[PDB]
Amino acid sequence: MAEITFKGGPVTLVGQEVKVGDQAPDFTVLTNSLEEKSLADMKGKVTIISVIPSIDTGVCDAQTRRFNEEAAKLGDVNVYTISADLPFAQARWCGANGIDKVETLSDHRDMSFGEAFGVYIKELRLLARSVFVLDENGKVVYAEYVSEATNHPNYEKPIEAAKALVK
Image 1: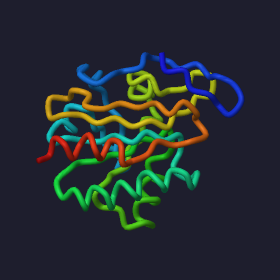
Image 2 (image 1 turned 90 degrees about the vertical axis):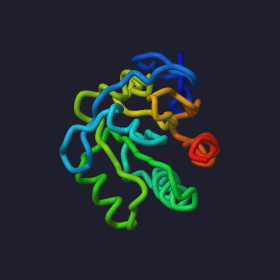
Image 3 (image 1 turned 90 degrees about the horizontal axis):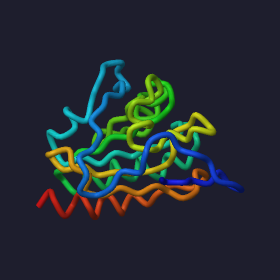
Image 4 (image 1 turned 45 degrees about the vertical axis):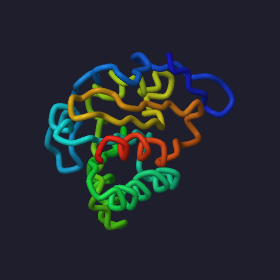
């Protein structure tokens, strides 16, 4: 189990902690454009996934935006962000920042993602801050679950996993 804290005590997760080498669960989220997208689409490249609770929190910036730049520096990767937040809030955050290498997505709807990857925090109904990397087979190449929901992963980590495979 990933057992995340919420700044003073533990909080339960739905789902299980996934690992490297495992086949990713394969679900659907909405695009920020209000269409279904699933892991089956994402396997078209080595893909990084950046889970955050909602996009407005400022700490989300340090992920989605840095990921945009780092993905440009890699030159050949694919990256998405997923929130329990509105598709249009997510689209807008991208538009404000001029993001192009990353696209934001909304699990908001059916939580299928947050549930299956064990990042829906049961006790909050909120997505964890976590990251994953996925091979073109849809195998997990890296996974990390920030032990503290009030803190965020380092984007360098899934970059180092993805950059090893895009060569």
